[PDB]
Amino acid sequence: DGASIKFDSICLYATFFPMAHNTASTLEAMLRNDTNDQSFNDYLSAANML
Amino acid sequence: FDGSIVSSYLTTRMPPWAGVRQNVMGSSIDGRPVLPANSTTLTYETVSGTPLE
């Protein structure tokens, strides 16, 4: 019943940290390791059958 | 007559943006209608709009 929507320019908004040039490369190499990598999942990561 | 003068009181520094010296809209930045340089309406985002794509 008669309604519309239209949009154009969408931007990214990173609010990370004002970090060092010194520690950044040092902190990068630890996560760049083959041994330690970012693990992520859900509390409910279950599949459903409808 | 007043206490003010030709070679007058010095001001401590000079004020950084354009608007410390005006109170005029008719001459504004690429607009027909513009909200005044001192008014109450200027303190809040009066979003100008029309349908885009």
Image (cartoon, rainbow, N blue to C red):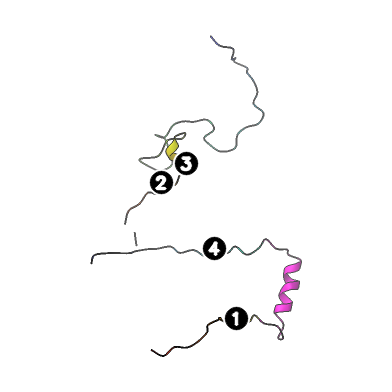
Badge 2 marks a residue whose secondary structure is loop
The kind of residue on which mark 1 rests is Phe
Asked if B4 appears above or below A5 in the picture, the reply is above
Label 2 to label 1: alpha-carbon separation: 43 Å
Taking A29 as reference, is B8 above or below it? above
User: What residue would you read off at disc 4?
Assistant: A13
Q: Residues within 10 Å of mark 4 (few under 14, many from 20)?
A: few
Q: Amino acid at mark 4?
A: Tyr
> Is B17 part of what is drawn in magenta?
no
Mark 4: which secondary structure?
Answer: loop
User: Badge 2 is on which residue?
Assistant: B46
Q: Amino acid at mark 3?
A: Thr
- Camera-nearest label, 4 or 1: 1
Q: Residue A6 occupies which quadrant of the picture?
A: bottom left
Question: Which residue occupies the extreme bottom position in the image?
Answer: A49
- Subunit under mark 1: A
Label 2: few (<14), some or many (≥20) within 10 Å? few
Residue under numbered circle 3:
B43
Task: Tell me whether circle 2 and circle 3 mark residues in contact (CB < 8 Å).
Answer: no
Give the left or right position of residue B48, taking residue A26 as reference.
Answer: left
Q: Between marks 4 and 1, how big is the CA–CA gap?
A: 22 Å
Q: Residue at x 45, y 64 (%)?
A: A10
**Mark whose residue sits in front, 3 or 4:** 3
**Going from the N terminus, do you reach mark 4 or mark 1 first?**
4
Give the CA distance from mark 3 to mark 4. Answer: 25 Å
Q: Are marks 4 and 1 on the same chain?
A: yes
Q: Position of residue A24 (x, y in %)?
A: 72, 69
Mark 2 and mark 4, same subunit? no
Q: Provide the residue designation for mark 1.
A: A40
Q: Which residues are magenta?
A: A18-37
